[PDB]
Image 1 (cartoon, each protein chain N blue to C red):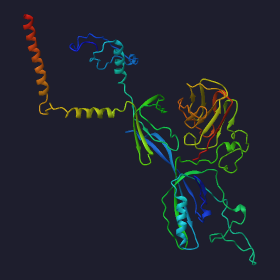
Image 2 (image 1 turned 180 degrees about the vertical axis):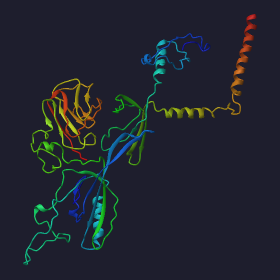
Image 3 (image 1 turned 60 degrees about the vertical axis):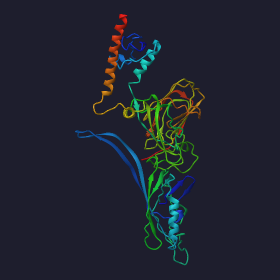
Image 4 (image 1 turned 45 degrees about the vertical axis):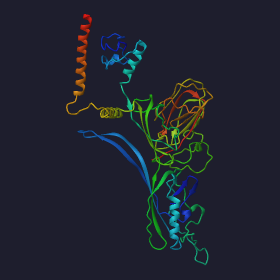
Length: 314
Length: 177
């Protein structure tokens, strides 16, 4: 219940700004269907079906000490939130409906009050809220009205909306999973084994014709807009270079001659032959990680493969 | 294509018929033959002929393009370039050339969308150019009379045959002397 927003150049959270929130409700993704009805047949063909948009709603109110200040506070809200600038929203929850604790009415152990006139139930460090999950959402704002209930309390009804892709982009790459350097950004929503360096954590293999990958993301990383990015030290010289993959298509690189120690950066629908001067004419096919086991099969025992990606959720 | 200007069918001048590779499965068809021609050599008569062939099995790909600015910016489409398209679930990975492009630019010269056509420019635009050529070639003339046309053409043609008859008379009368 804070509605964190990471904008291009800053980080903001509402309750820091005197802005309590009632709740956050996140719709699912609007499935746009594409059916076609045959003329006299009791059944209609599915041309397609496709996720579109994940409309968020967040009603937030605010109290202040005096009626004038309402105006300022409201303006702050707009200047703080209503941003066409695609932002990264992060949801927050509490772990408990906190109450005031027992005290002693002996002219001592009195109660605290926040900067806003409320009772601080958060006595200890471990009371305040948490990033409930290690993911974000690429988000933009839609119109709000501000009904002023009595006093200094005024409500607002934010209506956020997904920007590019209706998915729960996981923050942090898969290499931070590999190297346990960055802390946070890994919630139990992702069923992740502790065996760092073990299987289903590793995306850095060496000297293999074929290997195994566990894509922890329920949603499939077929869309190029996702940050799926591979880089391979090819290991062995060749004239052509095929690699296959399951839950995806076959990939070739024919017609250009390579060398062993040369490396390929295989970005989404894009191929850096040696990091620059992209040679992407050969078999334009992009790979697709669906969920769980995504087994790959090279053909000449690359001396290194490693690939970072982002986990996406539905 | 080498018979003289005054013959028109006594088919001297490199009589030949060619065909493409796909013929053998489709079979016997043929287009309007290369009747008009004053070209001597035979090297020409195969090039122009196969060009008349391969221009006709027409493929117009009037796809739509949508510009990505934050990503893939290095795709400013320009006409008369090579491009490698590939549509899955279509049976298509070949490369083609642009023949038409259609840009829009609101303000700051930022693009909003593109439209393009590949290979031949369209079926559509071919029809429309045909119509407009008809409608402008006509009304540029002056012989046209919508009420009973062909007086202007039949007067001419009958005059031509009449002078040919007079020329026949002259030929006989001169060969007499």
